[PDB]
Image (tube, rainbow over all chains, first blue to last red; front, top):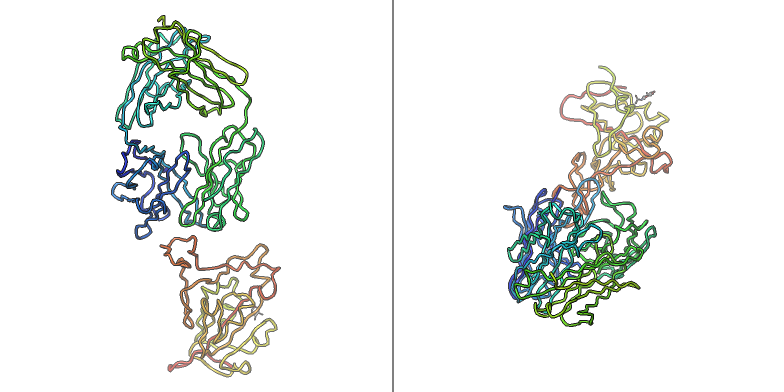
Amino acid sequence: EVQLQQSGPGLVKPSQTLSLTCAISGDSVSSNSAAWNWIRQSPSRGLEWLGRTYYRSKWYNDYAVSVKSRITINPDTSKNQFSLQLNSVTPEDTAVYYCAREEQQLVHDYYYYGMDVWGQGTMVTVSSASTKGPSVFPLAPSSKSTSGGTAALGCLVKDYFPEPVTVSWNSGALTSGVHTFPAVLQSSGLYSLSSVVTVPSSSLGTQTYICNVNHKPSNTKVDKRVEPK
Amino acid sequence: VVTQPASVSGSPGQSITISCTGTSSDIGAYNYISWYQQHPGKAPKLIIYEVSNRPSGISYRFSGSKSGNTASLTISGLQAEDEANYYCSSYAGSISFGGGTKVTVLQPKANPTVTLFPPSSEELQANKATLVCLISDFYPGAVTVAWKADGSPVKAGVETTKPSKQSNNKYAASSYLSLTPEQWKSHRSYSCQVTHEGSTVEKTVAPTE
Amino acid sequence: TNLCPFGEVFNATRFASVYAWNRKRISNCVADYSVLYNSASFSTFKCYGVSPTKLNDLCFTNVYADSFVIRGDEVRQIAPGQTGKIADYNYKLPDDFTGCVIAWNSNNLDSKVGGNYNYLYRLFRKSNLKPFERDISTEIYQAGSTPCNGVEGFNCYFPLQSYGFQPTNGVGYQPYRVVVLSFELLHAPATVCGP
Ligand SMILES: *[C@@H]1O[C@H](CO)[C@@H](O)[C@H](O)[C@H]1NC(C)=O
């Protein structure tokens, strides 16, 4: 299994340089048969190729014309990674950025598969506002949240910036009946989000419930115990 | 620049075909055309390479062809898991993606589950009051949320999300009513009202806690 | 002296691909050359720098028999001063060639329904062969401007090409077994002659 571990989400302030790292494992960054690409995606722009770095005896770079003057991709044989740098960012650079491997088949018949393996993507938001961690409030289960022996309980992840937030329950042990709702953009330009698990109300007295809110952009993690009342 | 239709819909069992059209310098230049499938919040996956090649793991329900300056993808036996974005891409030194096609798998109507949470005593001690109205499991993706206090319609302080695709192709939404702790105490009733097709579903909370 | 093993060459069960042509040194023996000329089995029997008649009245330090398989169309290239894929990349005869070229149709033995892919020829090469050279190299041919790095693929081809001989092909496209006799006279005592 070839896997691409990417560089964690955050905020780049305007006019600064964007910098991301893709770490390969299960393949060599200097592969005969590979190329290491960066691709970004925005809801209004779609998938946008940024460029590639490949090693065929010598090292090589292709870039896309819309970024040719602002971009640098940097392989690292030492660490088995390659990096992306984009200068002089503006809100137009807010996007999810992906690293992908372009793979050619060098055995029997040559095949050109394209982007066969993708990193999970890191969201970069370019904004002049500052990162803010969430405040997490318990949405308590109550006999007024039960419908036939089911209880709904939740965490209100309030007033954070930028995105994203990831929410787990009971450190990832509780996954069935979990519903995490996409965030609302408040008129303050801060985000809020709610996450709920449906659980047997008969387990409220025997099972502890904890939502684990991770906000990588602010190196903050909050675990909030949700008790009934 | 490579054109795809924005949106395609279909019923289970039917067959669908996404057009991908460009120029002699993009799609018709070579036969290095690839198609990708993307579910929301996940990375794209190669499902077709070289116009018609299925990578190992992809069902035969996925077919690919090319004619002239139009490559094209086809999904037979449309299953609910086929709801996703789809993109063609073409190699010519540089790499061009098509603008994307959201593929919907038609489903029967479903009415929403609605859950209303009052403000937590923790948020109230921080001089804040948020009512949270959670709407899930409805189809199609369009709802109307109204809020009322002591029976009277309320517009000040409401923020409601666009519907978003769940993993069962149904839709979720959420709506928040912001108040001060005093207004939360100055009324004896607050309600979230969710309308969808015909149905309306209304839930009420009261500050006696 | 004893007789020369022409059967070992002509009646061999499998012949070589033209790119990997076989040579047999005939020496210290006696051999009749007339029967072959009136063998009633040779589609081609050209001789160069020597007589097709009474050739048996002669002598040579060494005789070389070079066997391989090519198409009927290409037999015309097994002659001095010829050009084509075979003459240029596979088997080259010098301008001053002294010997005979004997060819015959082997469709019954060498072609097969669905193709006989054992018979190969060099389709790509950086330069033309010098007379009597032999390239058994299987190095990847760089057709594009960008280098191959020994990896086959796009613009990077395997040099050898198969014939895929089928019996239904035209007579021009059928396999032909070829034996090229070379008569060598050196400034040393002779070894092969016999009337
Ligand atoms: C080849 O074989 C036939 C019999 O199968 C024989 O009559 C003929 O003399 C042989 N040819 C040579 C060149 O020895």
